[PDB]
Structure formats: C-alpha cells, structure tokens
Amino acid sequence: KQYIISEELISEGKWVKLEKTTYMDPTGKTRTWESVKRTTRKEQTADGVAVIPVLQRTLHYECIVLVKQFRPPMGGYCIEFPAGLIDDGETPEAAALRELEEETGYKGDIAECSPAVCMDPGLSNCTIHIVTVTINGDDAENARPKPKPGDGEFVEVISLPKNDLLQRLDALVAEEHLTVDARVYSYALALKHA
Amino acid sequence: KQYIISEELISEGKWVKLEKTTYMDPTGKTRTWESVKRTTRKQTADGVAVIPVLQRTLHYECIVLVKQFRPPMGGYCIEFPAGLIDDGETPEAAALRELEEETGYKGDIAECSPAVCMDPGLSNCTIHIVTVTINGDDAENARPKPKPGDGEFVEVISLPKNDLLQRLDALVAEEHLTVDARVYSYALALKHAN
Ligand SMILES: Cc1nsc(N2CCO[C@@H](C)[C@H]2C)n1
Ligand SMILES: Cc1nsc(N2CCO[C@@H](C)[C@H]2C)n1
Ligand SMILES: [Cl-]
Ligand SMILES: [Mg+2]
Ligand SMILES: [Mg+2]
Ligand SMILES: [Mg+2]
Ligand SMILES: [Mg+2]
C-alpha cells in the first residue's frame, strides 16, 4: 500500500543528513516525514554491526561482554554491545569479529548473523546486523585481551554473567550516571522472561 | 572525564534537529560529533516501547507486535508497539495508551525500565521499555479495538514467545519486512537463555 514519493535533502553533514520524505498513505493521501540518514552507507547490507559476545570458559558461568564509552549524542556514558560501522567491502561477520577485537581485545567465533534490523525506524533508516559470537575464554589468545582502539575510540570492557544480566545492569545504573542501550536491555529482559 | 563543551545547531525541522557537538576526549583533545535529537522532548525519555505478553489459557504465550510503513526506512517494519510520551504523561500510562491505540489490547504493567538509548552513536533518543501482560481471556480483550491517532496505519502481528526468533526470520524471508533491533535482540535472548 504505502511507498515513498520523494526524498528531499534538508541538511547534509559529513556523517549524517536530514531529509524531507514524501510518501503515500494507505488512504491514497500524500504526507511528509522528517528522516535521518547516515552519509556513510555504500553497498553494505546495513550501516553497522552490533556484536552479542558470549564469553565461555570452563568452570565459569557464561558472560555477555559489554562496552562502556562516552557517547557525544547522549552527553554521557552508555553501556552497549560492541559495535561499529561496516567498512566498504567488508562482510557483516568480518566487521563484527574486527570490532569485537578492536573494542574488547577478544577474538571470537561467529555463531549467527541476523538480517539487517532497524535501529530507530520512526526516525532513521539506520540498520545493523546483530552478530552472535562465542569467545573461547580458555584459548590463550583470549587470556589477557588488550583492546586496539582506533583514533578517538576510548572503550572500557564490562563482562557480566548471562544468568544475572538484568540485575547486574540495574546495579551499574544504580551506582552512577550511565545509560543502558535499548538492545542490551531488551536482551537482558528476555533472559529474565525466559 | 569526557564531557560536552558545546553544541551548535546545524538544522532544525519540526520533529528532528541535527547538531554539531564539541567534546573533550579523555586525553584532553577537543573533538566534534554530528548528533541527532528530537525537538519534542520536554519527560523521562522521548518514547515508550511495549513488550506485550498476550496470555491466553490453553494457548502459547505470544508477543504482540506491530507492522507499519516507516518513511525513514522506505518500507514496512515489525516493531514493539511504541510511541512518544505526551507532556505530563508517565512512562507507564504512555505504555498502556500506546498499547491500546496500536493493538486495541488492555494490559497490566509488569515492569518498567529506566531510560534506555536507541542509537547513542547517532542520537540522544531514549525510551522506557515497558513489559505489560495482557489477559487475553478477559472480555475487554476478546475483540480488541485499535484506536489509531491521525496518520497511523498499524497491522497487528502476534507471535508465539517460544518460537519468536524463527517466526520473525520467516516473516523477513517471506514478506520483505525489516524487524526492529530491540525486537530481534529480545527474540535472540529467548533462544540464548539457559
Ligand atoms: C520524525 C518525524 N517526522 S514526522 C513525525 N511524526 C510525529 C508523530 O506523529 C506522526 C504521525 C508524525 C507527524 N516524526
Ligand atoms: C555521527 C557521527 N558523528 S562523528 C562520527 N564518527 C563515527 C566514527 O568514529 C568517530 C571517529 C566519529 C568521527 N559519527
Ligand atoms: Cl512477563
Ligand atoms: Mg564502536
Ligand atoms: Mg569500533
Ligand atoms: Mg507507534
Ligand atoms: Mg499510537
């Protein structure tokens, strides 16, 4: 029923643009929308990846490896799955393993890779693949993992037990001003509700 | 140790603006970020998203989702019922109201998250994730009456909680739809649990 009629640039930055979207509503009437897009998306199947990294080690409870970074759009520190944009010509799997190593030091193994999923579809066209990766924490490669942050990346690694994820996030949010990411919170909620 | 120095308006629509954020990196170097914000926040958060657990006896529990044309995406998305919180509305009340407008179901609050971020590398947008149960055997939910506001066009899709991820993959495979990242994250953790 509905479709895009036109997309008019309002303002293009170096990384993000705002567009005026004209579309057809399902009563055959024309409406507009204000749309955000990134300027960085080429032929990638999505803008980015987020990595669900399951750290597995003998005689440990499985942990979910999270990162804490300052996020200038938020004006504050945020707790998130490891994530980054997919480089031109890079596969979502390659992006995920690379980002995970850059941000956490860990060398993972791919488990699964989602289709492109929308970040905030009432606002932007931004998409990611959500990639599940297991980390063999008994491998010597992963013994004392050192992050390799790129320029202007400053990331702290926080591993929390899967079996208590939501409570452990609640405890961190209680102890300081930080925001938990909605996908991390959603995943912790489902772990509770299962 | 990181913080915002200043924000420069780049461009301001009715619903969204783009800003150039200056911030101090943790070495003491000054850096810029292109940040998106909504103009509508006044509020605990911009929005709510509702995780609606439809409970009917002798049936699988379902998670109730919505499918809607999203102009930023140029296509149809599957998402948790959701909307912006009205000035003076609580996150709980926004949840029950949006759930009702979009699905016609009347539900009870189970739990309510703190403000969580939607896309913190790009925007300051936040929501409250509100878990709501719906007593599907109650007369008020027998023939659920969706009350959409102006310009909303919402299809209701209820999926069993126990096979959520496989059911969503099927919809994507059959229907050229984009699943929301929070929905997909919750679906993932249902499978990953235990
Ligand atoms: C980002 C953006 N562009 S238009 C918009 N809306 C505000 C909420 O109500 C919708 C019917 C529509 C007018 N939000
Ligand atoms: C939206 C937006 N504004 S600046 C940005 N960048 C994303 C890549 O990492 C940083 C080095 C930074 C320059 N993304
Ligand atoms: Cl529940
Ligand atoms: Mg990153
Ligand atoms: Mg990175
Ligand atoms: Mg809505
Ligand atoms: Mg609504």
Image (cartoon, coloured by chain):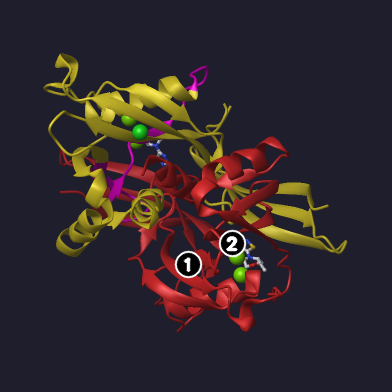
Chain colours: A red, B yellow
**Left or right relative to A38: residue B64:** left
**Magenta region: which residues?**
B66-90
Query: Looking at the image, which is closer to me, A83 or B45?
Result: A83
Q: Secondary structure at mark 1?
A: strand
Question: Along the polypeptide, which appears first: circle 2 or circle 1?
Answer: 2
Q: Which image quarter: residue A148? A: bottom right
Q: Which residue is pictured at 54% across the width and 69% down the height?
A: A58
Indicate the position of residue A123 as horizontal and vertical percent values.
44, 47
Magenta stretch contains residue A80? no
- Ligand 4 lies under 8 Å from the Cβ of mark 1: no
Q: Amino acid at mark 1?
A: Val
Q: Secondary structure at mark 2?
A: loop
Q: Please identify the quadrant where the C terminus of chain A is shown.
A: top left
Query: Looking at the image, which is closer to me, A41 or A61?
Result: A61
Q: Which residue is pictured at 38% across the width and 49% down the height?
A: B186
Local crowd size for mark 2, using a 10 Å CA cut-off: few (<14), some (14–19), many (≥20): some
Q: Chain of mark 1?
A: A
In the displayed structure, would residue B182 be above or below residue B135? below
In the displayed structure, would residue A14 be above or below residue A180? below
Q: Which image quarter: residue B145? A: top left
Q: Which residue is mark 2?
A: A13
Q: Which residue is pictured at 47% across the width and 34% down the height?
A: B47
Magenta stretch contains residue B87? yes
Q: Which residue is mark 1?
A: A49
The answer to whether the residues at label 2 and label 1 have Cβ atoms under 8 Å apart is no
- Ligand 2 lies under 8 Å from the Cβ of mark 2: yes
